[PDB]
Amino acid sequence: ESADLRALAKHLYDSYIKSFPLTKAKARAILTGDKSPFVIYDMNSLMMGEDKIKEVAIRIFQGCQFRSVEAVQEITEYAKSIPGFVNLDLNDQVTLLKYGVHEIIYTMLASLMNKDGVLISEGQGFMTREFLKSLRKPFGDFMEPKFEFAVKFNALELDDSDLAIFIAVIILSGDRPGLLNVKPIEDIQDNLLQALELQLKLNHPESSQLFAKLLQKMTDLRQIVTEHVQLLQVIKKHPLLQEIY
Amino acid sequence: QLNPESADLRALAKHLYDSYIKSFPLTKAKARAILTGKTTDKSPFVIYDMNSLMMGEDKSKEVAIRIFQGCQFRSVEAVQEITEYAKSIPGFVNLDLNDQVTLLKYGVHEIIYTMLASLMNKDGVLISEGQGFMTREFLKSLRKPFGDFMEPKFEFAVKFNALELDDSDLAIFIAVIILSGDRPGLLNVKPIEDIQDNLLQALELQLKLNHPESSQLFAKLLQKMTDLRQIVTEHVQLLQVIKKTETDMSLHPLLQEIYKDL
Ligand SMILES: CCCCOc1ccc(C[C@H](CC)C(=O)O)cc1CNC(=O)c1ccc([C@]23C[C@H]4C[C@H](C[C@H](C4)C2)C3)cc1
Image (cartoon, rainbow over all chains, first blue to last red):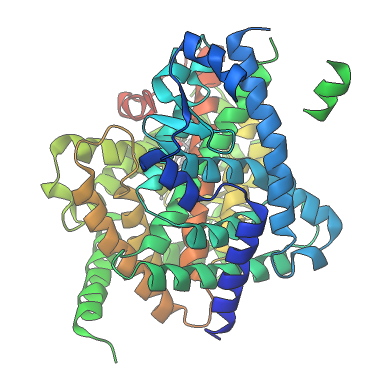
């Protein structure tokens, strides 16, 4: 029973390394200690950034969109390495990804955040929190909720081996609307839940009920997403490019 | 074996169940017993249409409104009851006054909708201490915006009731709901988290022992917290609209203080 669960843990972790270029391990190294990133702290510093790495605030947002679409391909490859996933009804796989990705993006985005800013482009840059907060409405509020969540989320001190399994748990959520066959999704999630429990007990013996606390964060994650999606539609204020993004 | 520290957790379990039973009149057990015909004396008058609604009133303005005004005052009671239960949670009354208020402000609706689920099945919901049963479709027939305020509540109830929890499982879970450390504006978060740590341990155990054959009930239950939170967010939305269309509808000042800047 409990050796199957380390396999699953190990399998997911290795797949997490293959699929994601910038790991929490690597992200944490850059936010702390020889090859620092370029800091974007104000209007002028963002200018030289493009030189290095319509208007300012729109050009940032679009940057998040290119990024996001890349992420979605990374998350999709990962998912397909989660056992059982690819033997599910295809409409469900697409449903699971369609509804899961925002939740995964802001989870892993936390890896790239401290209470002062977020690392960008493979950790070549850092965009400060108070700068993003200065951007003209409605963009100034776009990232603060994410920052508020990353503070809370990062306090759990999870590492990549923990996060890998968590992500799979998010993917395999059997409450997504319009799913045709929920049984095996729940069956896989149960198994992922067991693996996560054990992982967190063996990797963080001293953190009591870390499993519980981590799952509780799901509640804040989904608010984050609903809120952000609202913002997006409100934000409707190149043809073939629109289509991509 | 069960060990000394799990002994303490089982004790916490008992205390809480007992307080739950003392602070809440209609338990899930009474609810089920009414809804599933264990009954020649406990059967409810069913409301499902306008005349039956009229016939029910032995046991004024207009209907959709009169129903919501009823929900208002019953929720006010519930807040009292939950406040009573909260006091009994070891540690809660010792916290900073302001946090006490904060935790009830955000806990209360999530607990109401957890317990409303015990009084529901797919076809309707018990009302008035379980003497009446108001059908789901009758509620849906209510005029906009009111035919929309309870569906989301049913969708959750049928999902939630599928976990098959009992009052002794619910007592610990509602404690966990109240003592949550990521509520906005709390002064001191560590104390609250240490209490929840204990509550979560107790729950984890109670579920294992009470439901030994169900895999990961603990987790599955914690996941339902996201559903509650979305029910509460959507509810508050809908209040906003009611206030604007019905300029003559009174809201209770207690409930208004809870909704204020959620
Ligand atoms: C164990 C805790 C039970 C808590 O019950 C409820 C709590 C809250 C709500 C929604 C409220 C809306 C303001 C809220 O979420 O704040 C809705 C409910 C459920 N409603 C009722 O229990 C209820 C419904 C109708 C009535 C009647 C009784 C009688 C006179 C009048 C008209 C008609 C005949 C229905 C009210 C009384 C209670």
